Amino acid sequence: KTSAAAQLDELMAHLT
Amino acid sequence: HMANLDRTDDLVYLNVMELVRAVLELKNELSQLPPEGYVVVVKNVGLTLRKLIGSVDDLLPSLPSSSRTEIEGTQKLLNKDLAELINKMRLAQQNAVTSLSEEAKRQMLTASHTLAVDAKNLLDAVDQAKVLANLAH
Protein backbone atom coordinates (compact mmCIF):
# COMPACT_ATOMS: atom_id res chain seq x y z
CA LYS A 1 0.00 0.00 0.00
CA THR A 2 1.29 3.47 -0.95
CA SER A 3 0.82 6.58 1.18
CA ALA A 4 -1.65 8.08 -1.32
CA ALA A 5 -3.73 4.90 -1.36
CA ALA A 6 -3.83 4.70 2.45
CA GLN A 7 -4.77 8.37 2.81
CA LEU A 8 -7.64 7.84 0.35
CA ASP A 9 -8.92 4.69 2.04
CA GLU A 10 -9.12 6.71 5.26
CA LEU A 11 -11.33 9.21 3.43
CA MET A 12 -13.57 6.55 1.88
CA ALA A 13 -13.94 5.05 5.36
CA HIS A 14 -15.56 8.30 6.52
CA LEU A 15 -18.24 7.77 3.87
CA THR A 16 -19.00 4.09 4.48
CA HIS B 1 4.39 13.03 -34.24
CA MET B 2 1.98 15.34 -32.38
CA ALA B 3 -0.92 12.88 -32.65
CA ASN B 4 -2.91 11.80 -29.59
CA LEU B 5 -1.51 8.82 -27.68
CA ASP B 6 -3.02 5.37 -28.32
CA ARG B 7 -5.34 4.83 -25.36
CA THR B 8 -6.30 1.19 -26.03
CA ASP B 9 -4.66 -0.41 -22.99
CA ASP B 10 -4.22 2.81 -21.02
CA LEU B 11 -5.65 2.19 -17.53
CA VAL B 12 -4.68 5.60 -16.12
CA TYR B 13 -6.43 7.31 -19.02
CA LEU B 14 -9.53 5.14 -18.64
CA ASN B 15 -9.74 5.95 -14.93
CA VAL B 16 -9.11 9.68 -15.41
CA MET B 17 -11.93 9.89 -17.93
CA GLU B 18 -14.22 7.86 -15.65
CA LEU B 19 -13.46 10.26 -12.79
CA VAL B 20 -14.20 13.31 -14.98
CA ARG B 21 -17.46 11.66 -16.10
CA ALA B 22 -18.43 10.95 -12.47
CA VAL B 23 -17.89 14.64 -11.66
CA LEU B 24 -20.07 15.56 -14.64
CA GLU B 25 -22.80 13.26 -13.30
CA LEU B 26 -22.65 14.90 -9.86
CA LYS B 27 -22.75 18.36 -11.45
CA ASN B 28 -25.72 17.44 -13.64
CA GLU B 29 -27.99 15.90 -11.03
CA LEU B 30 -27.06 17.82 -7.88
CA SER B 31 -29.87 20.38 -8.15
CA GLN B 32 -32.61 17.73 -8.21
CA LEU B 33 -30.96 15.34 -5.74
CA PRO B 34 -32.55 14.65 -2.32
CA PRO B 35 -30.29 15.10 0.77
CA GLU B 36 -29.85 11.35 1.36
CA GLY B 37 -28.34 11.04 -2.12
CA TYR B 38 -25.43 13.42 -1.51
CA VAL B 39 -23.25 10.64 -0.09
CA VAL B 40 -24.01 8.51 -3.14
CA VAL B 41 -22.67 10.81 -5.87
CA VAL B 42 -19.65 11.73 -3.77
CA LYS B 43 -18.79 8.14 -2.82
CA ASN B 44 -18.98 7.33 -6.54
CA VAL B 45 -16.51 10.09 -7.37
CA GLY B 46 -14.34 8.77 -4.55
CA LEU B 47 -14.60 5.20 -5.86
CA THR B 48 -13.31 6.26 -9.25
CA LEU B 49 -10.46 8.21 -7.64
CA ARG B 50 -9.52 5.05 -5.69
CA LYS B 51 -9.09 3.16 -8.94
CA LEU B 52 -7.11 6.00 -10.53
CA ILE B 53 -4.74 6.10 -7.53
CA GLY B 54 -4.41 2.34 -7.89
CA SER B 55 -3.64 2.43 -11.61
CA VAL B 56 -1.05 5.18 -11.16
CA ASP B 57 0.51 3.26 -8.25
CA ASP B 58 1.02 0.22 -10.47
CA LEU B 59 2.57 2.29 -13.24
CA LEU B 60 4.90 4.43 -11.11
CA PRO B 61 7.76 1.90 -10.79
CA SER B 62 8.17 1.82 -14.59
CA LEU B 63 8.23 5.62 -15.05
CA PRO B 64 11.47 7.63 -14.85
CA SER B 65 12.59 8.30 -11.27
CA SER B 66 12.54 12.05 -11.87
CA SER B 67 8.83 11.80 -12.78
CA ARG B 68 7.60 9.87 -9.75
CA THR B 69 7.64 12.51 -7.00
CA GLU B 70 5.62 15.14 -8.89
CA ILE B 71 3.11 12.46 -9.89
CA GLU B 72 2.95 11.40 -6.23
CA GLY B 73 2.25 15.02 -5.29
CA THR B 74 -0.63 15.20 -7.77
CA GLN B 75 -2.07 12.01 -6.27
CA LYS B 76 -2.00 13.70 -2.86
CA LEU B 77 -3.58 16.81 -4.38
CA LEU B 78 -6.47 14.67 -5.69
CA ASN B 79 -6.87 13.23 -2.16
CA LYS B 80 -6.98 16.79 -0.77
CA ASP B 81 -9.58 17.73 -3.40
CA LEU B 82 -11.75 14.75 -2.50
CA ALA B 83 -11.47 15.64 1.20
CA GLU B 84 -12.69 19.12 0.33
CA LEU B 85 -15.64 17.74 -1.67
CA ILE B 86 -16.56 15.43 1.23
CA ASN B 87 -16.43 18.38 3.60
CA LYS B 88 -18.79 20.39 1.33
CA MET B 89 -21.10 17.37 1.02
CA ARG B 90 -21.30 17.18 4.82
CA LEU B 91 -22.14 20.89 5.01
CA ALA B 92 -24.81 20.40 2.34
CA GLN B 93 -26.21 17.56 4.44
CA GLN B 94 -26.11 19.60 7.66
CA ASN B 95 -27.90 22.49 5.97
CA ALA B 96 -30.40 20.45 3.95
CA VAL B 97 -33.33 22.33 5.53
CA THR B 98 -31.64 25.70 6.18
CA SER B 99 -31.00 28.85 4.16
CA LEU B 100 -27.35 27.82 3.71
CA SER B 101 -28.36 24.85 1.53
CA GLU B 102 -27.90 26.55 -1.83
CA GLU B 103 -24.48 27.97 -0.93
CA ALA B 104 -23.28 24.58 0.38
CA LYS B 105 -24.35 22.87 -2.85
CA ARG B 106 -22.65 25.60 -4.88
CA GLN B 107 -19.44 24.83 -2.98
CA MET B 108 -19.88 21.10 -3.66
CA LEU B 109 -19.96 21.87 -7.39
CA THR B 110 -16.85 24.00 -7.12
CA ALA B 111 -14.93 21.33 -5.18
CA SER B 112 -15.97 18.63 -7.65
CA HIS B 113 -14.85 20.77 -10.59
CA THR B 114 -11.43 21.28 -9.01
CA LEU B 115 -11.07 17.53 -8.56
CA ALA B 116 -11.77 16.89 -12.27
CA VAL B 117 -9.33 19.60 -13.37
CA ASP B 118 -6.57 18.15 -11.18
CA ALA B 119 -7.30 14.67 -12.56
CA LYS B 120 -6.60 16.00 -16.07
CA ASN B 121 -3.33 17.45 -14.73
CA LEU B 122 -2.39 13.99 -13.42
CA LEU B 123 -3.15 12.55 -16.87
CA ASP B 124 -0.79 15.10 -18.49
CA ALA B 125 1.92 14.28 -15.93
CA VAL B 126 1.62 10.55 -16.56
CA ASP B 127 1.61 11.07 -20.35
CA GLN B 128 4.82 13.14 -20.05
CA ALA B 129 6.43 10.49 -17.90
CA LYS B 130 5.63 7.79 -20.48
CA VAL B 131 7.19 9.88 -23.28
CA LEU B 132 10.32 10.51 -21.21
CA ALA B 133 10.50 6.78 -20.40
CA ASN B 134 10.55 6.03 -24.13
CA LEU B 135 13.43 8.47 -24.43
CA ALA B 136 15.57 6.70 -21.84
CA HIS B 137 14.86 3.38 -23.56
Image: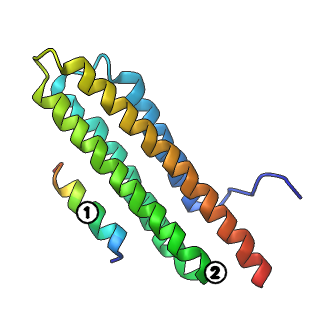
Which quarter of the rendered picture does the C terminus of chain B lie within?
A: bottom right
**Residue under the point 52% across and 67% down:** B71
**Residues packed near mark 1 inside 10 Å, few (<14), some (14 to 19) or many (20 plus):** some
Outermost residue toward the right in this view: B1
Q: Secondary structure at mark 2?
A: loop
Determine the secondary structure under disc 1: helix
Image vertical order of residue B75 relative to residue B87, above or below? below
Place of residue B6 in the rendered image (x, y in percent of width and height, measured from the top left): 74, 57
Name the amino acid type tagged 1. Asp
Picture quarter containing residue B44? top left
Judging from the image, mark 2 belongs to the subunit labelled: B
Residues tagged 1 and 2 counted as in contact (Cβ below 8 A): no
Amino acid type, residue under disc 2 in the picture: Pro
Image: B92 above or below B69: above
Image coordinates of residue B29 in percent, x first then y, are 36, 23
- The residue to which callout 1 is attached is A9
Query: Which numbered tag is attached to residue B10?
Result: none
Residue B38 x/y as whole percent: 23, 32
Q: Residue at x 68, y 57 (%)?
A: B8
Measure the C-alpha gap from mark 1 to mark 2.
27 Å
Which image quadrant: the N terminus of chain B? bottom right
Q: Position of residue B101 (x, y in %)?
A: 19, 20
Q: Crowding at label 2, few (<14), some or many (≥20) Cα neighbours within 10 Å?
A: some
Q: What residue is shown at x 11% (from left), y 17% (from top)?
A: B98
Depth order, front residue of B76/B123: B76
Image mark 1: chain = A
Q: Which mark is residue B64?
A: 2
